[PDB]
Amino acid sequence: SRMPSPPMPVPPAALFNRLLDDLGFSAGPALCTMLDTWNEDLFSALPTNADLYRECKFLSTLPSDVVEWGDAYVPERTQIDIRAHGDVAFPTLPATRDGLGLYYEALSRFFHAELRAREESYRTVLANFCSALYRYLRASVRQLHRQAHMRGRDRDLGEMLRATIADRYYRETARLARVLFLHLYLFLTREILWAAYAEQMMRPDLFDCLCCDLESWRQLAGLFQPFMFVNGALTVRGVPIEARRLRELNHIREHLNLPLVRSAATEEPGAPLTTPPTLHGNQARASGYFMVLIRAKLDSYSSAAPRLSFL
Image 1 (tube, rainbow, N blue to C red):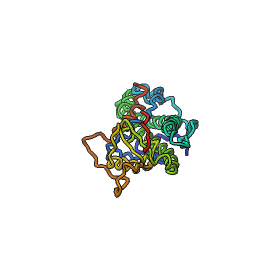
Image 2: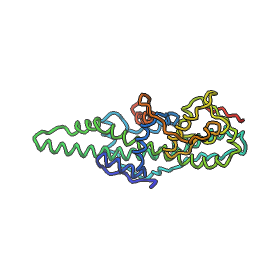
Image 3: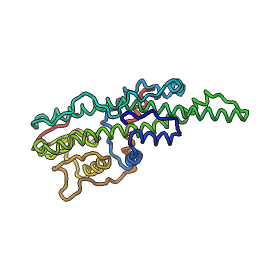
Image 4: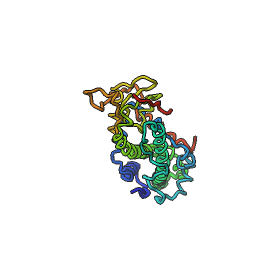
């Protein structure tokens, strides 16, 4: 449902499974696990939208703040549509090659508009999960207070509550947030990109001789690629990217169910389009770049255009 019902207070492992259900993301953990086996920075170029969480009190690192918010917050699944759209027009491929620059730009702007619009719903979903999380913690603490006092040891409930929040709440929220936002990004980029891929496939006249020069590899490794057919040449600061690198990147894109980035000029005749990269444990993992992305959202409360030519 575009508007899943607010979860019920349950043990973190049940709350987590419940989240996968609300998102139809049973694959989430497995996708999460894959992000470790890779070293690619697929998330840095993504908008953090940290501003959307700046006033989210359930993210306050002050346990007393979480107590105030949580006691008062009544979860609502009214204004929720996890597949909400923005009103920026989905760009159509230009009639001529001259419009390719405006297109790359317009498609990125569309993506951002869609993301921000859909993100407001994901924020409500997080609030609901944090609320059920807070309530389970409050219920456990009430029960411990009962048993203890029953044994002559009467402790301060309020102190107990604030301590478990410090102890468990932030760690649990982070775990939920990771999969929640991985769903936001994966589902949206897939949705937009598969539709645009199909169209670009049908426009050989724009992409057969397209040469695109990027400032960095990070700009190409990022999930959202406006161009999926760059057949004339694909270079970074003038140097032709390596065939093997593109192949490995494509293996990742493929394993995330995203369309591949095609380059006649790059691909080696006789080689596959994808190739499993060898993990280098002495290097940062894709999972690392993702956590930096999510942490910008979580820490909020308590805190170039490609050169295009043709052959």
